[PDB]
Image: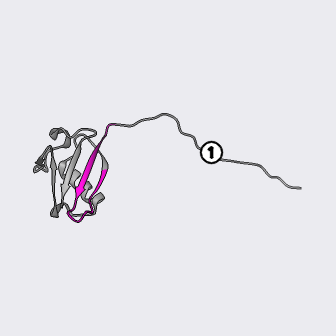
Amino acid sequence: MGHHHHHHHHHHSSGHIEGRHMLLTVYCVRRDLSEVTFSLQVDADFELHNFRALCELESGIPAAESQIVYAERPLTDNHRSLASYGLKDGDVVILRQ
């Protein structure tokens, strides 16, 4: 005697979506030749305030001990969004510690 059955489970995916985002390149320079460059995914309306915090996170050096420059000018206004600086996909910023 005996009563057994078989069972299974499975999962699938379909479709593709990317939303709306953009990639910016960051080049962090230390005079100690510990300079590094990377890129970050951000929203168009992302604050410069939040963007510099992401730069601090990935670079491992405080934003408080550095300044960030774009189009040869420092980005002084934390309350400007990246799109308002014209910082669009593929553009590059330079951080100086």
Residue range (magenta)? 20-38
- Numbered disc total: 1
The amino acid type, in three-letter code, at marker 1 is: His
57 lies above or below 86: below
Q: Residue furthest right?
A: 1
User: Observer-nearest residue: 15 or 21?
Assistant: 21
**Residue 31 x %, y %:** 20, 63
Locate the C terminus by quadrant.
Answer: bottom left
User: Observer-nearest residue: 84 or 59?
Assistant: 59
89 lies above or below 95: above
Image-based side of 20 in relation to 84, left or right: right
Q: Residue furthest bottom?
A: 32
| Residue 22 counted in the magenta span | yes
**Residue 32 x %, y %:** 23, 66
Image-based side of 4 in relation to 85, left or right: right
**Residue 18 x %, y %:** 39, 37
Q: Residue at x 14, y 51 (%)?
A: 78
**Residue 21 x %, y %:** 31, 40
Locate the N terminus by quadrant.
Answer: bottom right
Residue bearing the label numbered 1 = 10
Q: Secondary structure at mark 1?
A: loop
For residue 64, which quarter of the picture? bottom left
Q: Residue at x 27, y 47 (%)?
A: 25
